[PDB]
Length: 299
Ligand SMILES: CN1[C@@H]2CC[C@H]1C[C@@H](OC(=O)[C@H](CO)c1ccccc1)C2
Ligand SMILES: O=C(O)CNC(=O)C(=O)O
Ligand code: NI
Ligand SMILES: [Sr+2]
Image (cartoon, rainbow, N blue to C red):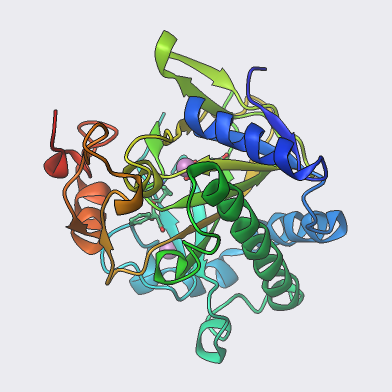
């Protein structure tokens, strides 16, 4: 496995160097000793195991007008079941916003299992906290002031809990800024561009896989790579994974961070509305970066 595993209790400068190199080379890495309670990660996975085992009577409560929603605008934050492209569906996703944790938002979350709201609220807070630490390591690697992304660029925090039914014998960037993913079974693969080859991202049940989204690829002016990754169906196990997809509010304007831009390293994208990007990203799957192709410049 060539995917870096970065221990967040090493000396501070080694963390920054390792994260920086991973962001430049792959756009994907794993973190361990990351400060999120292991007992909470286990409880959250147990919550989704139970949720996906509930009977139809419960699951229908998350299916607007009798069927799962699609990832299409407007992308609401209330909890809903989603599907995304059929295969030989292939994936059920429970998704909802998590930030800020409002009463009206929490009130849309599952009531069963009865621990869902307490466990997943605590998990959201912890995963967010860790996500903001990692962005700050990225700030130091890019030479940006700490806290640069602690604003509307991280205003939206979508939890996407995925269930992949087994089959005996899908690639994308995430369009947002940064994603943390918890898994405990093989199935996640990263595209190694230089070989045009898919490789396994080893499942470490107490680690988080960190992958950079298209928005960060653009804002770093391609100093950092976004991760192109996919999931292959498990031949034996139903697989569950928990993604926390953090990024801009839909009222944001995305552009290469001006402080990174020079005469020698000009901007590679013009500014665009995130909401306009989001529409293309969700609709046009003709290429991985179709969402940002209309904004490319200096090529
Ligand atoms: C596998 N798919 C991919 C990634 C997750 C899942 C569902 C969809 O991605 C999203 O819905 C996220 C939600 O924040 C998104 C939506 C608009 C703009 C930026 C990011 C596409
Ligand atoms: O489920 C996995 O292991 C990977 N999930 C995704 O890439 C996603 O939901 O965007
Ligand atoms: Ni993804
Ligand atoms: Sr139904």
